[PDB]
Image: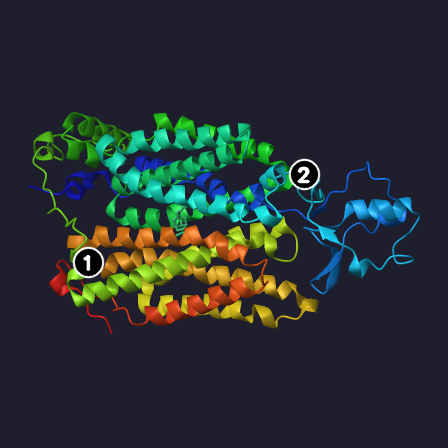
Amino acid sequence: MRDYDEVTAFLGEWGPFQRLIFFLLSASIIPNGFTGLSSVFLIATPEHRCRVPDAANLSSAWRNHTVPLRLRDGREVPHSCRRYRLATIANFSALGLEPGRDVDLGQLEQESCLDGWEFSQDVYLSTIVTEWNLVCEDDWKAPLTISLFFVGVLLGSFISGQLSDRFGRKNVLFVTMGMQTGFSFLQIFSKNFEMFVVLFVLVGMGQISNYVAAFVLGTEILGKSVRIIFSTLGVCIFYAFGYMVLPLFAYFIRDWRMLLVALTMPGVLCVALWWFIPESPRWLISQGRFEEAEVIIRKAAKANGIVVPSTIFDPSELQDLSSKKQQSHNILDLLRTWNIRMVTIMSIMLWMTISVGYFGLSLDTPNLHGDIFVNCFLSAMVEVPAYVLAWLLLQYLPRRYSMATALFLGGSVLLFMQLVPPDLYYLATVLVMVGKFGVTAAFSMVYVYTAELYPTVVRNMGVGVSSTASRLGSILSPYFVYLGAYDRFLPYILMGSLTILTAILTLFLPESFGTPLPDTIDQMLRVK
Ligand SMILES: CC(C)[N@+]1(C)[C@@H]2CC[C@H]1C[C@@H](OC(=O)[C@@H](CO)c1ccccc1)C2
Ligand code: NA
């Protein structure tokens, strides 16, 4: 018996086949870039105030003084959820009385907006918040939709695995790509809020599912050395490109339906890949469909120009491949021994906190100062050097000090936010981008570090548990942004404190660099 990576080693590590597969599977990750964080523009809240119908016979003075003024940022602004009793105002205006001259505005009665709201159109022409008035007593519905999107992503994480195992990688990939694109398109025709919410849940489910299927198919087709590069840089950078191009679209298109059309179109464009990506030969061998694997291997050999006679490859060996011992599935293994128990708890908390920080910072961009589109672009762009640095650090430096430093930077920088004087408000944006830089580096590194910490017997299970923890964290991530209304800096204080505690935690994990990866739990490294 032999190994699949050995039997197939004759194809080489790099060449026309593996190159095309690498850049096509990576290109299929772009739509997840602008689909993941489109909520920053689809669910944005413009400035708004109570609407006063023009039927009111109010003087120009009264029309200038129809809403109480409240102070924000040290500056007067119309109160966004309350107005002076329109009937009392109309009675005063009919009597000839005028504000200030005859009326003390400070003691008038107030009511909520019974004629709806007037949203400004300086930035957004329309969004779902303006469509269904998700403001004042409905404001909690705005982040809820985003939480529900990540809820769908959670469910997709469970389902896409089993589906891909039972029906293949390419089939699940393209089916869920089409599902995501179709439900993204359908959302344009949402009559009311509930249909939009449920369609957004399904869109997130499809998005996660097809990301996962692309990742698994790529890490199964590519060779041993290029596998790491694909997993680490290949998909991350093209996700960053998708995110970076999201604000480019949102700048020209400022209507949520036309923006959904624009973000839907690339998904339809990706369907051409069906004729270029083959099914994973390793999976087909797992199902016992050896003729299809043989055909795909011979086609790859022909594409790379390698002569493949019986002396260098034969299906008889293909039919007698080795199978690795099956890994434990019962979760009890992760809790049976004290050391692995503690390592699992720390990894859960580390992944959840890194995810909360990353998605909170991503979703908080429209609340920063300066141009919203420039801020979103800078947020998307600061990830590419974060991935390059993460990759170099993983290649050459111990994981513990690297991740302690990246988290310490990401957390400490945020705590400085409250110390920036308003005159130099732009420094706060600098800090926030450096903050997200650190978080992004840590987020890229943990995917590898955790996979090294667990022994083979349960490695996948442990990684999956920690990954689910991170995904749970992003359900909470839009609510930390929601807290920005109660107190501007509270979200950053929370994120910074939690990140510093996570950076302190990381130092207690055992070091893996430069040591053989363990095979059985008895060989697992001990926590400090
Ligand atoms: C930060 C880098 C390493 N990622 C490529 C990792 C973690 C975040 C980012 C994107 C990806 O994680 C996701 O969950 C993706 C695809 O499901 C996602 C992006 C945006 C919204 C929801 C999910 C995997
Ligand atoms: Na995709």
What amino acid is at disc 2? Answer: Leu
Residue 288: give x, y in percent of width and height.
Answer: 13, 30
Residue 330: give x, y in percent of width and height.
Answer: 16, 50
Distance (Cα) linking label 2 and label 1: 52 Å
Q: Is residue 181 left or right of residue 191?
A: left
Q: Is residue 316 left or right of residue 452?
A: left
Q: Which mark is residue 125?
A: 2
| Placement of 213 over or under 340, stated as above or below | above
Q: Is residue 470 left or right of residue 427?
A: left
Which residue is drawn at the image coordinates 25% and 44% (left, top)? 223
Q: How is the image coloured?
A: rainbow
- Callout 1 secondary element: helix
Residue 83: give x, y in percent of width and height.
Answer: 74, 50
- Callout 2 secondary element: loop
Q: Which residue is mark 1?
A: 334
Q: Is residue 217 left or right of residue 474?
A: left
Which residue is drawn at the image coordinates 45% and 62% (left, top)? 438
What amino acid is at disc 1? Answer: Leu
Locate residue 122: give its quadrant: top right
| Placement of 133 over or under 436, stated as above or below | above
**Quadrant where the N terminus lies?**
top left
| Res 391 seen here | no
